[PDB]
Image: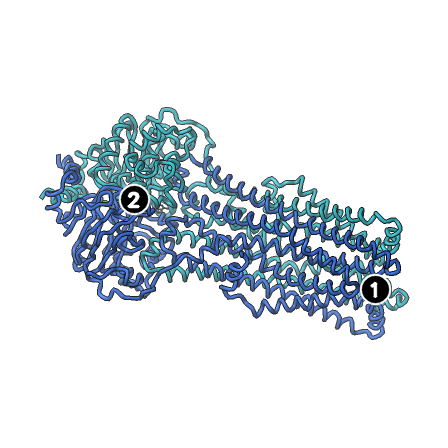
Chain colours: A blue, B cyan
């Protein structure tokens, strides 16, 4: 039951059949030439004298050789290119899947492993396709051709060796099971290794800042050592392919000599036929080696891509309903909305609010309270478990994700960046020609423009891995520029003013309230000093909205967490005193 | 000049010589058996009649076969295990290097690539060792054994084919150069793909939050397509290995027929010796194929590890001077310190300050001013370009890095986390048995303990990749717990209170000023409300300290950036009004 989804996976890409069947045909004609060679070996001794009397024909013979291996070389190319159209289809398929799974999969299942599947797993299926398909084709044809060659010289010994071949099959099966259960462990471990490694190495400042060079070389050596045990053990099982095959030859030989019991009784005359039989039975053993090597390699390749054949079945969702937002100037209403990441624990607990269109509503609350996960709810990364989100009595599930996510800008709490230019990280994802009057206006609105032009100017500047070649404030101002560039109807600032200074905070706040007066902005302030002019506040604590309304009536009406503002009062009051 | 550092790299690990030389010896005795076989093929025809008259000996013959291939199977194991002791030495060497380079290398050279320099390249080194080295050993002997076999039957034709072999060498050399310049491009490109890809995939919230599924699918496809250009082109060059070899056989054949000009003139009698000569010259062509396949594979493997043989030469530095810090309760003095990342641009510009031992000095300044890079200077991640840092008239370069970094707890601006338990990220790097009453004290001092125990309790909790299964405040409180756990003499808080709420800020500030009264804490506050009680302020702007001293005398004495405090006054003053 393992062979059918794997060959459906190979069928799912587009293999070069016009080269693959050509190389198959060349191997067929080559093996038929080698099968005809023991009929021409008796004619060589007079063909040599014919060539010496005739003269030039040996050059034609060289031309035949200059065809044959040369044509056989094309067979190798027509396999190898075909190999590099299967695996470079597989990544071209698998990487089309992986950036379309919903982000619940990437919360569950560590991305630093699932890079390994696109780039390590697909390259283990090279061996089965590049060489062993050749092996099984040539070998399968030879064993049937030499089998009918043994059949025309004897009937019942041919039936006997035909009985011996499924004994080789039934002794080959448990080696195939062991090869499967080793190759799956190998291509699961290599992934945890390209993950205990590429999770460590971006944090080299934390390895060096603690004293953990010796401890982390340790996790690494445990991994190199597990790949060495799960790969020397495969080699051990590979070493049982060699002698066991000889065992069945041993069986067949004793099966012959036992049949040669009544066979010598009828055939002390016909000993030379038995000599020719055991000679061809000595010839048969190398295509059987090719067949069993193909079967071990096929079990290894199925074991590698077993973890990958289920990545291609996980329900991407991107634009199925197609309905456009079409004005997206509506108030966003919540029903009784509840949501948890793990389905046992609820992190939003029957929340309900109304974000009114064209005013600033600010989510204020203590840490761990449910703010960023409410904003992940408000983008439908995640669907709620309870009742849903509407836009003017119309539920959000009817709109397409593509047309609705094109209207919402988001500065998340990490302010993420990717390697490339500053122009690339501002431009990111847009289909327009962003030009450079638009970027200048955007990065001037995010207070970025006065500090990029001291650096070498927006296209030479590379921000490195993870945005490490910029500061902790500069990368947040670039994330604000990314949100402000595409001119959203709804802006969402998951603490966008966290790691800025006070003067840059005032600048970005002035420019953002200038730009976004007529649209809906939802900000999160950890500290209440920047959202006193907000038109609505929502106090979110432990997944429950405990306060709602204008800041003045909320700080008059709320209980204990009025002090959560008042301490901030005291936190500046000493700076008065 | 390429072969010597590669074989010094293989010599630099510890290959299993006691198995490698054993497999070499088994291949030697097997090839000598195959060389003796054309002397025993005339004795088979009477050995068959001796076996029929004697009877049991064929079973002994089977035992010989049950030795030989079985022994040959051990040869395969003694190669393959040896292969998995070279490459699992290489990672065990290379990963010992990579976490010991200074972080200037990881600012220059993009760690996502360097992961596949330890995973996607040592495995390419694999084939040269596992199968092909056998080719050069079996072939190099068969060709010399069959060469002396041709030499005992003729002198000058043997000299002639001995002349033809360096023609094959000089036509093999440019194929080797092309294979080198293709394999280096392959194992440089696969690195940008394991890199581009594993820089994209942690930021799946940014890919989904923008609409960049189509655009980032279009970048991965350019990568799968360039790995297909370095792969359907290498295969093209390996398809030139096949026919070109036949060309030199063509040469040798015509060379024999060239000497056949005076050879048939003296040797129309001795045509049968020429038949045996051309027969063995037909036999010679497959070990030449083994030799040329080994040479192409060796050029490919050198091309892969050329980018890796220079990773092992980059000057790690960790504990060379050995002088342990003693009091560490000394005031940290600066000389004229200047530093820039790129050596043309200066980011610290002749800074000078005195961090006095046992008081709180706070670095306050505008963004991009040089604070976090001053703290990277104050850990000597980076040595300064100008004069250095001292500890009571004694320069910091005399102390060992290991004993001095064990006395400084640094919370970074990103608050980095790694996958594992919350206990693992708090414990990180320590050599003690930590003790749960100590982790409880630490995470209670960082205001973490009241929010971990709502989650499943400090060992079941996994924080996922990059700390994504915790919040933006919880992961910063865990980073503060990591700094507070190992009880440093100097604490360094690169904006440790950034993404917290106000009440948790007050709690962590109260507990930290309770714990660290007698030691040196250096904090960075983007907002001045938390460092008004600091014993010293340093205003850092554009890499120059422009203000220095107590907050009151600084805000009285400084010029324009007194307003940088005063706006914060106004930023709370409206919250009064
Ligand atoms: N996969 C996940 N991603 C994010 N949060 C998760 C996940 N699984 C569980 N959580 C829980 O969700 C909460 C974090 O989301 P939340 O919205 O509370 O952050 P937040 O309120 O923005 O925090 P802060 O305001 O301090 O940044 C935590 O209680 C955490 O335990
Ligand atoms: N490899 C690098 N790593 C960090 N900073 C770099 C690097 N190369 C250059 N820089 C420059 O260093 C400065 C960032 O360090 P700096 O100490 O100023 O950050 P910061 O003052 O902490 O910023 P903020 O206070 O806003 O977080 C920027 O001007 C940046 O251009
Ligand atoms: Mg910084
Ligand atoms: Mg958050």
Residue at image point 59% right, 44% down: A233
The reply to whether the C-beta atoms of the residues labelled 1 and 2 are less than 8 Å apart is no
Chain where mark 2 sits: B
Quadrant in the rendering for residue B391: top left
User: Looking at the picture, how far across and down is residue B292, in whole percent?
Assistant: 67, 57
User: Looking at the picture, how far across and down is residue B398, in whole percent?
Assistant: 42, 30
Relative depth, front residue between B17 and A16: A16
User: Looking at the picture, how far across and down is residue B203, in whole percent?
Assistant: 36, 52
Secondary element under disc 1, as helix, strand or loop, is helix
- Dot 1 alpha-carbon crowd within 10 angstroms: few under 14, some 14 to 19, many 20 or more: few
Residue furthest top as drawn = B327
Mark 2 close to ligand 1, CB under 8 Å: yes
Say which residue label 1 marks. Answer: B275
> Looking at the image, is mark 1 or mark 2 earlier in the sequence?
1
Quadrant in the rendering for residue A133: bottom right
Say which residue label 2 marks. Answer: B472
Q: Quadrant of the C terminus of chain B?
A: top left
Relative to residue B182, is residue A537 depicted above or below?
above
Q: Is residue A402 visible to us here?
A: yes
Relative to residue B432, is residue A417 depicted above or below?
below
Residue at image point 25% right, 57% down: A484
Q: Is residue B245 left or right of residue A273?
A: left
């Amino acid at each position: 039951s393992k062979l059918k989804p794997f060959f459906a996976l190979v069928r799912r890409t587009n293999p070069s059949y016009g080269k693959l069947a050509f190389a198959l045909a060349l191997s067929v004609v080559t093996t038929l030439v080698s099968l005809l060679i023991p009929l021409l070996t008796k004619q060589l001794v007079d063909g040599f004298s014919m060539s010496n009397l005739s003269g030039t024909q040996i050059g034609l013979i060289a031309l035949v050789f200059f065809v044959q291996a040369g044509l056989s070389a094309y067979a190798t190319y027509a396999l190898n290119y075909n190999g590099q159209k299967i695996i470079s289809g597989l990544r071209e398929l698998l990487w089309k899947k992986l950036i379309k799974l919903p982000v619940s999969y990437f919360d569950t299942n560590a991305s630093g492993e699932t890079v390994s599947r696109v780039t390590n797993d697909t390259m283990v299926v090279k061996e089965l396709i590049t060489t062993h398909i050749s092996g099984f084709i040539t070998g399968i044809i030879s064993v049937i051709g030499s089998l009918t060659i043994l059949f025309i010289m004897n009937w019942k010994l041919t039936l006997l060796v035909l009985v011996v071949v499924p004994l080789a099959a039934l002794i080959l099966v448990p080696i195939g099971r062991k090869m499967f259960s080793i190759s799956r462990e190998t291509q699961d471990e290599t992934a945890r290794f390209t993950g205990l490694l590429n999770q460590i190495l971006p944090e080299i400042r934390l390895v060096k800042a603690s004293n953990a060079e010796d401890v982390e070389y340790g996790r690494g050596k445990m991994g190199i050592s597990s790949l060495f045990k799960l790969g020397v053990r495969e080699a051990k099982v590979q070493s049982l392919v060699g002698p066991l095959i000889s065992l069945v030859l041993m069986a067949a030989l004793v099966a012959v000599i036992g049949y040669g019991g009544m066979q010598v009784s009828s055939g002390e005359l016909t000993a030379g036929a038995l000599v020719a039989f055991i000679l061809y039975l000595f010839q048969i053993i190398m295509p059987m080696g090719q067949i069993t090597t193909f079967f071990t390699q096929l079990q290894k390749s199925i074991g590698a891509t077993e973890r990958m054949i289920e990545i291609l079945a996980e329900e991407e969702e991107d634009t199925v309903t197609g309905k456009q937002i079409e004005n997206a100037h509506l108030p966003i209403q919540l029903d009784r909305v509840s949501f948890g990441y793990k389905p046992d624990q609820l992190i939003l607990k029957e929340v309900s609010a109304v974000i009114e269109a064209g005013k600033v509503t600010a989510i204020v609350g203590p840490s761990g309270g449910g703010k960023t996960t409410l904003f992940k709810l408000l983008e439908r990364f995640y669907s709620p478990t309870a009742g849903t989100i509407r836009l003017g009595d119309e539920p959000v599930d009817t709109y397409s994700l593509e047309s609705w996510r094109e209207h919402i800008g988001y500065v998340s709490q990490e302010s993420p960046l990717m390697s490339g230019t500053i122009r690339e990280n501002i431009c990111y994802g847009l289909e327009r020609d962003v030009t450079d009057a638009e970027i200048e206006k955007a990065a001037e609105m995010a207070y970025a423009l006065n500090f990029i032009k001291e650096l070498p100017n927006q296209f030479d500047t590379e921000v490195g891995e993870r945005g490490i070649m910029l500061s902790g404030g500069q990368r947040q101002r670039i994330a604000i520029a990314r949100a402000l560039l595409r001119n959203p109807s709804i802006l969402m600032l998951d603490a966008a003013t966290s790691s800025l200074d006070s003067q840059s905070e005032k600048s970005v706040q002035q420019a953002l309230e200038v730009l976004m007066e007529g649209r809906t902005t939802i900000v999160i302030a950890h500290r209440l000093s920047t959202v006193v002019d907000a038109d609505q506040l929502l106090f979110v604590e432990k997944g429950e909205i405990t306060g709602r309304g204008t800041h003045h009536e909320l700080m008059a009406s709320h209980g204990l967490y009025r002090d959560f503002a008042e301490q901030q009062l005291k936190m500046n009051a000493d700076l008065e005193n």
